[PDB]
Image (cartoon, rainbow over all chains, first blue to last red; front, side, top):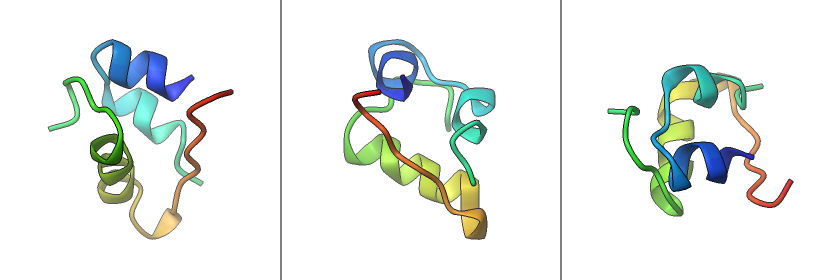
Length: 21
Length: 30
């Protein structure tokens, strides 16, 4: 999930944009 | 500003800024 990928580990623009509508 | 550890309201804030008028969905569990 987003928390594992962006909180627990360093986030990226690619991963953020996956959660845009 | 997105290449770092983003937790809680800070992560949600980043989604808000990046996604813009597209909006986003925030799912901390699944």
